[PDB]
Length: 599
Ligand SMILES: CC(C)=CCC/C(C)=C/CC/C(C)=C/COP(=O)(O)O[C@@H]1O[C@H](CO)[C@@H](O)[C@@H]1F
Image 1 (cartoon, rainbow, N blue to C red):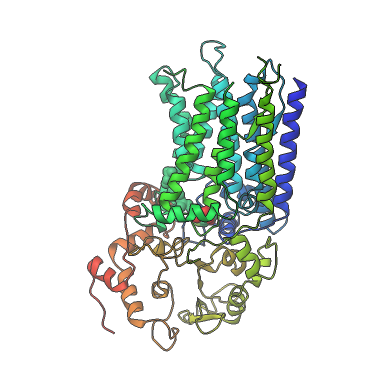
Image 2: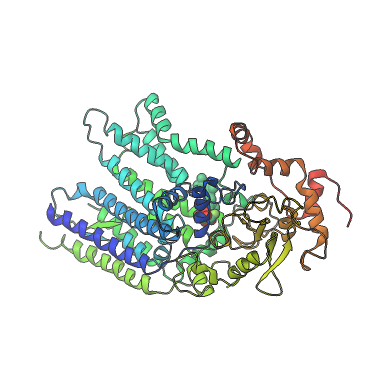
């Protein structure tokens, strides 16, 4: 009836407007949020989907947000791509919320066919309130595209579940089924963890197909683009994984650390009350072969199990330094099936059954009310590596809303990098100076005579910056200046580095600067390198990089691309992925088998 359709529309409009206003009132783009940006700039300048010119390191786990922002930046005439990232994050996240609302509305629709009820926003409303969700709806991270994808997939899965009406014996439109399969396949691309959902989404559809031929067709059509881009990834990167995810070696069974992260995430907002209350409310509302998998209860179980598995995977992998970025997706999955709750009357009219309202609207008030307390409650990010990155970068730079990459220049070491680069025109390896905030320069190898004069527009050497914060360098340093990270976000040598101790999460595997100065035309002798580096480590690392395996891995990720290079990378992606380099230069030279040079 209109009395319920309009109520659903008003709930969707209200939540979308509130969430969009909350996003626009916190314009934040993380340092990682500028990594996507860096890559897409390299793509729009003709250098392909790469982080640095020649260094084919895939620092974007999204594979769709990267290209979505690429398209946005292409169409945009304003030189700032940060505005593209902001607009796309807002729009995609708002669309995700709207789509999940409408999917839940369709899920509850069959129950309200003969009974008129007022939908109300719950579960998803608290998600809007939850400050991490509001903060991360704006950054250049995937939490906008992830929300959009989850909303779309939820709506399509609900449509498929209710689609079981036997129009011509197929129980669902062929085109709609194929498109849903395609979306489920794209889950793998959108975010590697989402593959779980994308897996569990496909199987539920596969088991719903009668004949093996139909299952084969569904799995092929649904997973054609993801497999094609996996082949392209193998080729243009030589890695089975994006490259960041490879920066973690033997990372598992961090149950204690993951539990600590979950408790930290729950503490400033008290998510236990929403969880308990929404579980009780969903149960109270619920108290009204292939056929049993293609049912709305099956899809609800799908979304709940997908959220639980996402949370379990995140705990097993350990929540990153982000306050709540990792847990937003599983939490959104949990809240999706109860994203909009109908106040249907039992319609057995004596009052005893009417108590439902007094015990189901009231619960929603105890939900929405908590939401009004959840947003307003400050979100704290004491030895744990969990820090609210939005607050960190707002109080680290000179601005409270660090939207543009020109705003990030106020960061302590990010004006100094530019001053040094224009100060030294013969190249340099820039490292964070221990004495002062400015950069220690290991000057690049002096350019050879007659090559300085044989250069277009004056000779500029190879500038290589080595610093933990990566994206802000990408969008402030310049397109042609190599950008590298200690952890291995965009450093091919660091990503392969093996780890000895668990340490901290997201920042433990700090590669030695000796490795960083090992590669590139950078001077080695003690007088020119900074004092606080060890020359012996530098020489040992340089001797280590010449080993056949590491040298071959680097060549396959830096040599000029071609058909032969693409085929060889596809063939040897497995070999390159399962190749770990010991952190200590001396122990590597022992492992690789090359002799240790004398001091
Ligand atoms: C199949 C399943 C379910 C399990 C394995 C699948 C898998 C590979 C696991 C997850 C990989 C992982 C840790 C990704 C972390 O991404 P993140 O730290 O956000 O990336 C940085 O943030 C920016 C935008 O994301 C990027 O520019 C930066 F790189």
